[PDB]
Image (tube, coloured by chain):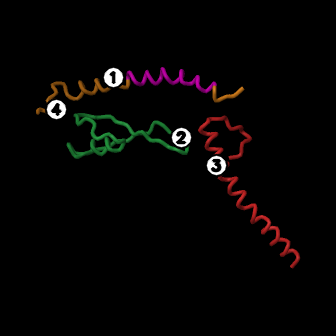
Chain colours: A red, B orange, C green
């Protein structure tokens, strides 16, 4: 049960970061679309 | 008011068609003459 | 970006085809003529702006 409790505490720690990551996703959607409409050459190493 | 002269054409649709044909003479050359010239915009897409 | 698309149509003489096509881009009416005609579709995407 120690492994299970470690897993569940790790995921509940992830729970709070879920919403910050979601707002990061939204702001980066905004930023990427802005950069596209600013027409910047995305490097080959850019991850879509 | 009379709209049948196209069928009343003594030489058939050819006289019309050639007229229409001259269209993608002109415009085609136009876009061709534009295309390579427009190509210069790529210089900005490629930052220093 | 996509470009060079094309649309054809048949409609019987005076079937409102020109009226529909001119309404697509917003103009009330174009010109009802004879032979092949020509018009626009001004397609705007906000995502690509």
Real-space Cα distance between discs 2 and 1?
Answer: 35 Å
Question: Which badge, 4 or 1, is on the more N-terminal residue?
Answer: 4
Q: Is residue C47 left or right of residue A24?
A: left
Chain ID for label 3?
A
Identify residue for label 2.
C49
Residue A5 x, y percent position in the rendering: 84, 75
Provide the secondary structure element on which disc 4 rests: loop
Real-space Cα distance between discs 2 and 3?
Answer: 14 Å
Q: Which residues make up the magenta segment?
A: B25-43
Q: Residues within 10 Å of mark 2 (few under 14, many from 20)?
A: few
| Image quarter (top left, top right, bottom left or bottom right) of the N terminus of chain A | bottom right
Identify residue for label 4.
B7
Image quarter of residue A15: bottom right
Q: Nearer the viewer, mark 3 or mark 1?
A: 3
Specify whether residue A47 is painted magenta.
Answer: no
Chain ID for label 2?
C
The furthest residue to the left: B1
Chain ID for label 4?
B
Real-space Cα distance between discs 4 and 1?
Answer: 21 Å
């Amino acid at each position: 049960t120690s492994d299970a409790v470690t897993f569940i505490t790790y995921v509940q720690s992830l729970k709070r970061k879920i919403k910050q990551f979601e707002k990061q996703v939204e702001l980066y959607r905004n930023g990427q679309r802005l950069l596209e409409k600013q027409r910047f050459q995305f490097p080959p190493s850019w991850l879509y | 008011f009379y709209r049948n002269a196209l069928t009343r054409m003594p030489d058939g649709p050819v006289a019309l068609e050639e007229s229409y044909s001259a269209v993608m003479g002109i415009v085609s050359e136009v876009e061709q003459y534009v295309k390579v010239w427009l190509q210069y915009q790529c210089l900005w897409d490629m930052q220093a | 970006l996509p470009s060079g698309k094309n649309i054809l149509v048949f409609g019987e003489d005076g079937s409102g085809k020109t009226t529909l096509m001119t309404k697509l881009q917003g103009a009330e009416h174009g010109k009802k003529g004879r032979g092949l005609e020509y018009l626009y579709l001004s397609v705007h995407d906000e995502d690509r702006d």
